[PDB]
Amino acid sequence: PLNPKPFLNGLTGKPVMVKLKWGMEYKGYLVSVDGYMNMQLANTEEYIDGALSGHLGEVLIRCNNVLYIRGV
Amino acid sequence: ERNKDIAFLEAQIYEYVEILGEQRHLTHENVQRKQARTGEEREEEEEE
Amino acid sequence: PEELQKREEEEFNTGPLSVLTQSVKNNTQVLINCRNNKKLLGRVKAFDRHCNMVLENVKEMWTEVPSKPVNKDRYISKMFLRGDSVIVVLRNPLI
Amino acid sequence: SSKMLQHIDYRMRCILQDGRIFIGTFKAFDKHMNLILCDCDEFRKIKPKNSKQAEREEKRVLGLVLLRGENLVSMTVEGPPP
Amino acid sequence: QKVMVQPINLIFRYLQNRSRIQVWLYEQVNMRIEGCIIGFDEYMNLVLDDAEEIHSKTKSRKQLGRIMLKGDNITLLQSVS
Amino acid sequence: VKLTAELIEQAAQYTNAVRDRELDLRGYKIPVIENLGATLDQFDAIDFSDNEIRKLDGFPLLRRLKTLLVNNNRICRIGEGLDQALPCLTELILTNNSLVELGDLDPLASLKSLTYLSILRNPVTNKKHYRLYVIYKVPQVRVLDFQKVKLKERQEAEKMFK
Amino acid sequence: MKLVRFLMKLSHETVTIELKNGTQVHGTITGVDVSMNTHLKAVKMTLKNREPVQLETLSIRGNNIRYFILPDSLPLDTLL
Amino acid sequence: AHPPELKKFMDKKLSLKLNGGRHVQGILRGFDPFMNLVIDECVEMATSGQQNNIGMVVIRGNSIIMLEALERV
Amino acid sequence: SIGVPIKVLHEAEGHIVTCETNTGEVYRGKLIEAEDNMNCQMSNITVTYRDGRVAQLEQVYIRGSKIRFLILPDMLKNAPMLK
RNA sequence: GGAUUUUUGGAGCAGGGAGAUGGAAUAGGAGCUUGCUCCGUCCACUCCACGCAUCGACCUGGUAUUGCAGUACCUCCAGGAACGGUGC
C-alpha cells in the first residue's frame, strides 16, 4: 500500500513529470504538495507534445488541472 | 495627402492642451496626491 | 481563529502557494495561465486558499487567429481574478 | 441583503452555460441558484453554416421549469409581474 | 436485506490482488491509463505502477511508470487481469 | 378612446392556447394603432378583437411576433410598410373586415416568412379569381383561409393575368 | 483571508466582469455575496463575438465569472 | 451526503450512460453516496458494434449521466 | 435546510416531468422519485437522444449533476411554495 | 462550506482536397497610384467522399379513420430534401 499523500510526500525533491489534463507537461523537482494537492515544482521545463518547449523554472500548478503526476 | 489628418490632429492636441493647462496641472496634482496615500486615505477620497 | 491565522501564514509560507506569498513579499510579477489561454503578467496584491487574486499592472497576452495568429495583448491595470480559472502560476517570468 | 429576492416574480431572462436563454417568470430560488421559472421559453442560437444564411433563434415553450444552478450564468429582467 | 459492494472495497481488492487496472478518463474517450494500483485514497486519487497511456486513435501505448492519476479524471476502473 | 401604452401595461399578458406569448386587447374600440414598442419584444401574438381600426398601420419594429389577430375590425385600407417592422410573422388573421378590391391585398406579398392567412368575412372574397390571385400574389403562404394550397391552384394562379 | 470579503465591499463601483463563457459585462456593482454572485446595474453586456446589448440589471452567478476589471481609482490597501 | 436511492437497481441489469458518449451495461452490484457504481458482468459497448466484456468495474459517479433499468426493478 | 426549488421538484414527483441532461438528451417521463441533490428516477421515459432519436426507456435514473433543467408540469404553478 | 448531482468550471480551438472558376461598390501589402503579378480571411456552383448513416419536425399527390378528451409525437405509400442534433 502506498497512498497518494505518502506517495507525494516521498516524491518531493525528485524530478517529477506532471501532465495536465490539456496536453501540457511539466518536468521539475516537486517542492511541496498540500492536502488539496496544489503542486509546486522547481526548475520546471514545460514540455508540450512530449517536446521540450519552455523553461518556466519555479512553478505552482493548481490542483484541478493535474491529470497525473509521475516520477522521472 | 496621406499624413494630413494626423498632422492636423497633432496641432489640435497642442492647442487644446494649452487651453486646458490649468486642468492638466490639477490632474497631475491629483495623481501625486492619490499616489502618496495610505489604504484608508485612498478609500475615503474615492468616497468623495 | 487565531491559531488558524498562524496556521495559514505558516502554510502559505511553506506550502504550494509560497510563490504567491513570494509575489507579495518582494512584489515581483507572476505569469498566470488561464483556462481561456490568456497569460497574465502582473503582481499579486492578495490571495487566498482558492488562488483568487487581486492583481496590479497586469499584461494579459493571448494569441488570436484572424493565416498566422497574432499576439494581441492588453493592459489591465488592477483586477480581481477568480481562482478556479488559474492554471499555472510561475513565480519568476523570464521577460 | 438577499438581492435575488428583489428580482422575484419578474419576467426574467436567464443565460445558461451552453448559450441558451430562459425567459420565464422567476418564482423561486435557493442557495445553489436553482431557478423556478413559470411560463418559461428557451431560446437557442442557431449557427448559420453558410456565407449568406442568417443566424436565427429557435424558441421552445417549456412551462414550469426547474433550472439547476450549475447551468446558470447570469440573469436579467425582461418585464413586470404579469 | 441486501449487502452492497461499495466501490472502495473493490478498489482495495484491486490493490490487494495488485491487478493491472485500466482506467478510463473523464471527457477523454481516446486515452485510457492502465497500471498496477499500489495505492489510492479518499478522493479516488490513484497511484499506479508501470502505468501507460493507451490512445485508442493512434493505438499506441506510452509507458509512464509510477503515476498519481488525480481522482476527478476517472470515469471507470477496468481490470485487464 | 385612443390606444396608448397605458392600455398595454394593464392588459392581460400570458401564454396563449397555442403556447406563445400573448397580449390581449379585446373590446377596447381602438381606432388607430400606435405606441406598441412598449411591449419590449417579449411577445409572439397580439390579439385585436373588437376594435374600430380603420387601417392596419402604425406598426413599430417587433421582431419576435409570429401572429397578428385582427379579428372583427374595420380595415378598409391596409398598411404597406409592415414587413420592415414585423420580420418573422407567420399568421395574419384579417377576419371580418371591409377589404373590397384585389389590389388592397397587394401589400401582403412583402412578408417573406408569412405562412398562414385568414381573410374571411371580407368583400374581397366575393370577387371571382380571388384565391388564385392571392396565391399568385403572395406565394409564400401555405395555408389560405384554412384551406391548404394545391398545385392545381398554383398552376391556375400562374396562368392568369400573364 | 478570503478575497470574497474584499469583493463584497464593492457597491456602486463600475467594473467589467469577464465571464467564463467569453462574456464581457461592464456595469456598476449593486451587490456581491459570499458566493461571488454579482448583481450589476447599468449593464453593457457583450457575448462572445456578438454586439454589446444593454440591460438595466444583471445577476451573474459566482462560478461563472472568470475575472474582474476593477476601476483604477480604487485604494485596495484600505480595502484589505 | 445522502446516498442515492439505488436500492431498486441493486443486482439488476443496468445500462449506464457515461460521459463522452460511453455506454456500459451490467448488473449493478453496489454504490456509495458519490454514486460511484460497482458493475458486475460489465459489457462496454463502443461506437463500433462489438462489445467488450470487462467484467467487474468501478464507475466514478461524476461521469454517469443516466442509467436505464434493463430489468423491471 | 432545503431550498424552495428542490421542494417544488419533490412536489413534481408522481407527475410527468421532462429532464434535459447535460448531453442534451431529453428524458420526459413520470417522475417516480426525486432527491435533494436533484437525482431523478423516472418511469415511462421517452428519450430524444440529441439527434431526434425518440426511444422509450423504462425506469431510468438520471444523475442530478448532469441535469440541465427540469420542465415540471404546469399544474404545479399554483403550489403554495411558489405562492 | 475549491475532490463525482448545482457556486471557484473539462474548457479552449479549427471546419476535407482540387480546378487557366467568379466578386472586396467605400477597406490589404509588395513590385513605391491607375492596369498587371504574387501571397496567410467568405459566399455560389461543379468534381472526388450530394461529407457519411440515424431519427424528429416539414412539402406535394394518392389513401384510411367520423372517433367526447385533457397530450414528448401520432395512419400508410413514394419523391424531395430548406432545419435540428448524435458517432466517425
Image: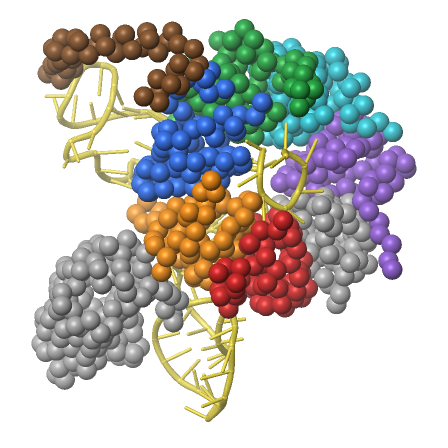
Chain colours: A cyan, B brown, C green, D orange, E purple, G blue, I red, J yellow
> Residue visible at 45% across and 60% down?
D38
Q: Is residue I34 above or below residue A70?
A: below
Q: Is residue I74 above or below residue G41?
A: below
Q: Is residue A39 above or below residue J7?
A: above
> Residue visible at 32% across and 21% down?
B48
> Is G65 displayed left or right of G26 in the figure?
right
> Residue visible at 39% across and 53% down?
D10
> Is G19 displayed left or right of F14 in the figure?
right
Q: Quadrant of residue I43?
A: bottom right
Pick whichever, F95 or F149, lies toward us.
Answer: F95
What x and y, as percent, mark residue F108?
A: 18, 66
> Is F19 displayed left or right of F29 in the figure?
right
What x and y, as percent, mark residue A25?
A: 63, 22
Residue extending farthest to the right is: E17
Residue F158 visible? The answer is: no
Q: Quadrant of residue E71?
A: top right
What x and y, as percent, mark residue C10?
A: 68, 14
**Figure quadrant of the C terminus of chain H:** bottom right
Q: Is residue G77 above or below residue J37?
A: above
Pick whichever, F160 or H52, lies toward us.
Answer: H52
> Is F82 displayed left or right of G70 in the figure?
left
Q: Quadrant of residue F125?
A: bottom left
> Residue visible at 33% across and 8% down?
B33
What x and y, as percent, mark residue F140?
A: 26, 66
Residue D3 visible? The answer is: yes
Pick whichever, B32 or E35, lies toward us.
Answer: B32
